[PDB]
Image: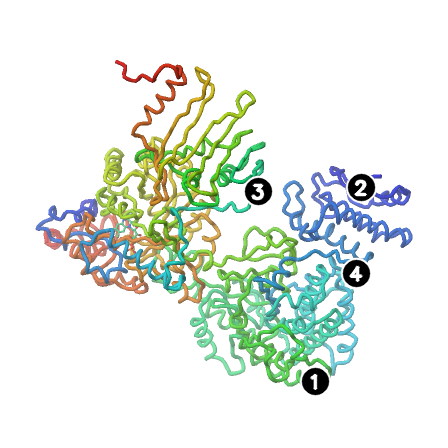
Amino acid sequence: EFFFKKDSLWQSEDLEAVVGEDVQRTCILHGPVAAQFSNKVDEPIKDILENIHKGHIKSLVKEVYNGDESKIPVVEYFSSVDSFSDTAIEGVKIERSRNTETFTVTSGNVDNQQWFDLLAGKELSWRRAFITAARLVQGTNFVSNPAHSVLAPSKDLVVKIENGSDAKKTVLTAFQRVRGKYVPAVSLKSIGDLKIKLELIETRTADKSAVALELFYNYKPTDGFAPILEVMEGRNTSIKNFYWKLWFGSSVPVDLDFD
Amino acid sequence: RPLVLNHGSIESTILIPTTEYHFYQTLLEGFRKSLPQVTEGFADDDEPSSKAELLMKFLGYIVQSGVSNQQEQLAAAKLVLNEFESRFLQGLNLHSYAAILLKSETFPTTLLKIKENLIKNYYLGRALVYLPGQRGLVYPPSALLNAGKSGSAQIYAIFGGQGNTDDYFEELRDIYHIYQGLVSDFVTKAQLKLQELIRTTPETDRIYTQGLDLINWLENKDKTPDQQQLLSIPMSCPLICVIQLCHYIVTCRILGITPGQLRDSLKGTTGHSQGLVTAVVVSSADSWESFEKLALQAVEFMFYIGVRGLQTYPNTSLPPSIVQDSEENAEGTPSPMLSVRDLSYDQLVKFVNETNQHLPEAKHIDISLINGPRNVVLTGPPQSLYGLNLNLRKAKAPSGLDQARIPFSERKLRFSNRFLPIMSPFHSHLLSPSTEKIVADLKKAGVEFSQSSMKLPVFDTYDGKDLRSYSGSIAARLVECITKLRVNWELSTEFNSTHVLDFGPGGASGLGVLTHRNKEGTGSRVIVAGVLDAESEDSEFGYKQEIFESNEKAIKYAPNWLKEYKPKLVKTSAGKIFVDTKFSRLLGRAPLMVPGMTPTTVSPDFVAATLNAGFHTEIAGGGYFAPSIMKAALQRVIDQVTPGTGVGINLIYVNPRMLQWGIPMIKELREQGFPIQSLSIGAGVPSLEVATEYIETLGLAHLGLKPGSIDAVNQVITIAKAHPNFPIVLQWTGGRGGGHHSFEDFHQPILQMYSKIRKCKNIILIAGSGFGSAEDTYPYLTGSWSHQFSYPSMPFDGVLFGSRVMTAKEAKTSPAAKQAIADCTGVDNSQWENTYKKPTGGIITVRSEMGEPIHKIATRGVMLWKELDDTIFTLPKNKMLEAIAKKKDYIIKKLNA
Ligand SMILES: Cc1cc2nc3c(=O)[nH]c(=O)nc-3n(C[C@H](O)[C@H](O)[C@H](O)COP(=O)(O)O)c2cc1C
């Protein structure tokens, strides 16, 4: 019984190995239901499974959308969206004054999951795909999302969204307090299209002028499980350009062609 | 000036009287000794445990222990009443404030403390103040009844019958104790309706031995007859009807409305057998005097049914070897009503017929009322109902039959039958002689209901028709529906209801929780309307605190499963239609995936082919034997797939050797950063402690689980309820369709566990077991698969394709084996259990390496595998070797060919 029933599944894969390439001596696992249609053999996997998917879509259109495609709830990208319907966050001073949204978090700890809902809300733009993303793709590498760290609600923090309920011209800007004064810590905007620019700014530098660490990202709405990808082709110089002007002056040019 | 009324550890309760405090100082000096001493944490029942329970039993002191004049008793009572109605409860009324007071961790009060100290003493203060109750609209806007009056919250009333509880009188004792000021105008006039008009002047009377002093029994539990005189029909039929009408008088008096003002806020209002009489007086009441003139008619109605129903079938005593036998074989006392539950109707129609044939025509057993598809009661003579109780005893499974590791071989059924606590054969031929005696007796008095002064409908129990559009005497129809006609409860309650009110005499055991599974997932919250019991964490039935609510947004609804989990469509802004499903929201792809199959999803060239197609899959860990080769195979998916996509990992639980490396390798890959997004545990659910090392330590996005049995599905829920924020994906695969079994039917356990699964709102439910086309699995996405079992829509969150994927182009199965799958013919979802006898189009089951009924295509190798299992491989140590030695020449010809 050891020699008979052991490692007997791979002969279906290559049956050049079996004696005379007989298929009747192999062991192919198959459930009894779902075998009465399979006459189409050596079919691509994008056609075996999309035709089940397109066959469901065609059956839902005539059923719950009355045979009309114009009643589908058109979205920008497709992923999970969580419910935080009532705006009752604990410590905040939300005001909306003619496309400027100041969100001075007052005291304690707010719900962070509710905080990022306010931080990018009521649309499906690049901003909601950035602040509420659960993953960042570092070139086939799922890491934690940076917006849950650079925009984590600390005490006395303040963000200012310019026209986030208007268009693609949204400029989110988080301010924080050093030496009693509000300085522009974090900035965030959409340069070009399908490209996001996140720049973290430090004000205490060598020559006492603020320098910004420009980090760029991709944004594909065709994936919703991970819609944000950091571009990495040139960010190691972008950090070295940042730390040059911060350690040394902005007077001396950034020199990387050393020996 | 302030005033303290402390007790032990709570000093905070401060009322503000006037400056004339000589009266208040001599008030509380008796109150300071009136309450018992501190039970080290307020554990006594006569002792106040909250800040409000001190103020209310102080009010209960100054009303019940009245020593001064009435001018200062009345003034001090409404001073405590106003400081309580403006500081503790504001806006919301008493039991809604007592709802949140009971579930208070910082003050551990219980139910008998909160009803005796708080609820009872409040309505004593509401009794000496506002004595008739004709003014002073301080009553809050009950938002459930307001929404039912105008809105999409239609309310239906339900009235119980008989046999819900054996001690029904302790409900009437309880409502007369707490609400003594409310239900006393009716109970003193129902007692003087019975004993003064119709018990002193019937034709003859030896059936009321102890009299019917009702008021004397409620305040003195030593004058109450004990439990068998009370269950007797002459003083159980009027007394159950008093209990239901007292629950309707109390509910109309907490809200301060008339019975005709609660009437327009609902519709429907049917009853079971005994409560259909209560269903007419509710639907035809108009005012507080149109009610009482009509509520006493329903008492005089049920007096004649109880009296004449005993004179045509009197109670009898059974042999005590019959009674002691049934009481020790897990039933009750043999009574004329026996309730068979969880047995299908076409099986107990022949279990009755195989007992009725050995019996005379008079001693027949009739199916008297059908409460549901698996819930009927039977009715005959009690010695004859003990007849089929012995027949049912030989077709019942014991507690350890184990048709869960054994397939459907034994024909032992898992049901339960028990005798109801009813002392008369209702809805049978045994009581139908007492009909023309009653109709000619209701015609002697004015106990004919009007049939046109009822404004709500009343659904008949026999055929479900409305009683407003019924020609004939409606009182003569009501005795037909109790004495002889079968209660057909399913089509008597085939209405569309958002909430259902049960003023039953059972409370937490009445018609609400009894017929609860009849309308489980169609969005009808049943509200028991007689008991408070604010502990309600599960959401299958409400309580009396949900009749009234101040705000509209605290109305708890019921889970309409079709409405919540309906598949929808979404279109991106590039022209890509998805199917909006709870599983498809998790992946951002289509709701259909491919599991971790051992010979065919082991190749990285195929796993990457079905990931580029836009579908989820998982590379199986069964075909890998060391973490270095598996990590090099996981990487080989990531090269030939576009960046941003993830993989899944299927690890098998029944070898710890694969979990020796597999669980660490995922942890070393995730913290270094790798697109592994999922982990399914095949062939067994891990225990709760070892599961949280997979959720917390590994960086997975969602955990897959494949429960096979019905305890594993319960075991998944204890992992899901341990942390509700992680997407635990439940992959349900039955016996059919798979490469292995779950040993049971496919859609029998999820027909019972769909309600438990959907309460966990992080469990994603995925159907398996052999799907292969769009029309094959479309009843499973929409929920129209359970329609053929008289069940509601139970829709799935996506499905998964196993053996249908094996003949793909990129699948690494060989082309001679691909056509061997196509020439194999399939069976339907029903006749899959004939695999261990015959080839079902070319598929049998054999034992596994460790021993599992693994499905295979019936080729010549598997027919040899099957033959050696049933001739050699399932033999002992000693006997195997000579069966080898006998057929050694025969086996070798089979192995070589
Ligand atoms: C060839 C084959 C191999 C399988 N291997 C595994 C496995 O390794 N682990 C597991 O949990 N299920 C395995 N399964 C079962 C699948 O997960 C799934 O339950 C089954 O394929 C349902 O098939 P159906 O879609 O044809 O109904 C396998 C099924 C087949 C057909």
Q: What element carries label 1?
A: loop
Q: Dot 4 corresponds to which residue? A: B135
Amino acid type of the residue that numbered disc 3 sits on in the rendered structure: Ala
Marks 2/3: CA–CA distance: 38 Å
- Please name which of the two marks, 4 or 1, marks the residue nearer to the observer: 4
Is the residue marked by circle 2 packed among few (<14), some (14-19), or many (20+) residues within 10 Å?
some
Of callouts 4 and 2, the N-terminal one: 2
Task: Estimate the spatial distance between the alpha carbons at disc 4 and disc 3, rounded to whole Å.
Answer: 39 Å
Residue B238 in the image: state x and y as whole percent: 69, 72
Relative to B572, is B454 on the left or the right?
A: right
As drawn, the label of residue A88 is 3
The chain to which mark 1 is attached is B
Tell whether B246 sits left or right of B18: left
Q: Name the residue under label 2.
A: B5
Q: Is mark 3 on a helix, strand or loop?
A: loop
Q: Can residue B722 be seen in this view?
A: no
Q: Can residue B344 be seen in this view?
A: yes
Q: Distance between the residues labelled 4 and 1?
A: 40 Å
Q: Position of residue B84 (x, y in %)?
A: 76, 47
Residue for badge 1: B443
